[PDB]
Image: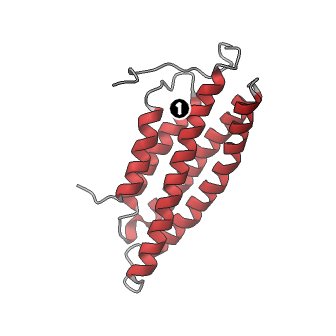
Amino acid sequence: NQPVNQPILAAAQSLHQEATQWSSKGNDIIAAAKRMALLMAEMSRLVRGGSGTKRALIQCAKDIAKASDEVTRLAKEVAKQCTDKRIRTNLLQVCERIPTISTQLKILSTVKATMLGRTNISDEESEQATEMLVHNAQNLMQSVKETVQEAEAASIKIRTDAGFTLRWVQKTPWYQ
């Protein structure tokens, strides 16, 4: 079908597996994380494209960074209502890593996009730029996955408020 950068696809699938165990209904962290995983999977295809995929590669990074701001914004709200200082601090700590990682995703996607369909660039420049993009994508997927898990852990420490708190409902059994 279409060539894909396996480690980016694997990082995407890893976040999606974790996010899809929960319902998006009344959980915008879950919705944004699912959008991020789906967009990151598109990225693994685009990173392998020609000159025509240059705009799509940079727009994909921009979309991923926008979905990560929704994750960060909501996780800060979860933290603000959490009574456990350990969980509250962890959530606030990860919220400050995500914008840095996603800024770096935009810079490395632009770097890779300038290289698509070019003949003058060496395999070394290309490989080095691709490896940097790969690591950044893995770090981002990991940070959001951990943000999902900590936001769920924080829910136990929050007085459930219908229409006012995040909703955690398993869509499928954990062992499926």
Q: Residues within 10 Å of mark 1 (few under 14, many from 20)?
A: many
Tell me the residue at 63%/40% (across/down): 70
Q: Give the quarter of the image for residue 45.
A: bottom left
Q: Quadrant of the N terminus?
A: bottom left
69 to the left or right of 116:
right
Q: Which residue is mark 1?
A: 30
Q: What amino acid type is highlighted by mark number 1? A: Ile
Mark 1 secondary-structure assignment: helix
Residue name at image x 38 percent, y 80 percent: 123
166 and 155: which one is in front?
155
Identity of the residue furthest to the front in this view: 86
Does residue 114 appear in this view?
A: yes
Would residue 57 appear left or right of 102 to someone viewing this image? left
Please tell me whether residue 117 is drawn above or below residue 139 in the rendered image: below
| Residue positioned 37% across, 75% down in the render | 117
Residue 73 relative to residue 18: left or right: right
Q: Residue 160: where, in percent of width, then height?
A: 67, 14
Along the viewing direction, whichever of 57 and 37 lies nearer the viewer:
37
User: Can residue 113 be seen in this snapshot?
Assistant: no
The part of the image, by quadrant, that contains residue 74 is: top right
Residue 36: x percent and y percent? 50, 44
User: How many numbered dots are placed on residues in this image?
Assistant: 1
Q: Residue at x 43, y 55 (%)?
A: 43
Is residue 22 depicted above or below 163 in this figure?
below
Seen in the picture, residue 19 relative to 13 is either above or below; the reply is above
Q: Position of residue 27 (x, y in %)?
A: 57, 26
